[PDB]
Length: 223
Image (cartoon, rainbow, N blue to C red; front, side):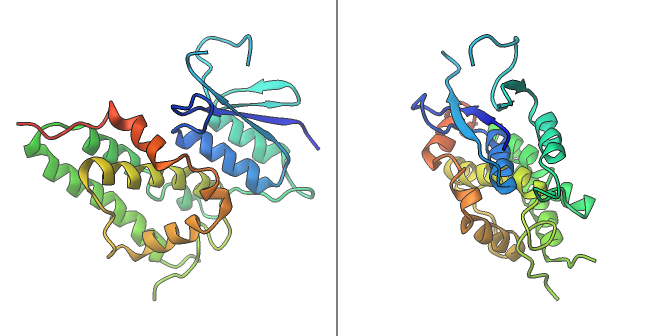
């Protein structure tokens, strides 16, 4: 019913889906809600007439611009509610903090250039992945076989985490030849399920685009 326009960040193409876990998050939320909406990319070096600082992702709801992904998310979950739509908010608040420290540890591990500091950072990263993995294997009120963070349905929690885990996996691999340990079966089951879902797969920018976005960010380890 409502008129929704999503404005995400553009990649190198300047006309394609660039790297941004936040744009992809909203994209996933909109998709899961079921509502109709359009998607428009935005090249930094280039809708018309906006406030200073407003950068993707942002949407237009009935011609009105909405800013701040977190504000947007709240808004959406609010207006796109029952009986017409399904609530996407997780039932367990802990589903919201699961793996929340991964992206930050990955950023430090990837931006570092000191060889002697790399070992501890990789250990720090594995540590955050370990906690997430344990959240995924621990049953919610043997090894849990549920498909996502909050149960067997995707929730706002997966929209927030999956895009980030994806960046983590692709970049860590490219710039550190790092692999999420297969011993972490929870993470892998979770990711497998996610990559088999169109809402996640069709909203992921390309590996190239994801890697490019970090070419000037990740550093080699130099003495």
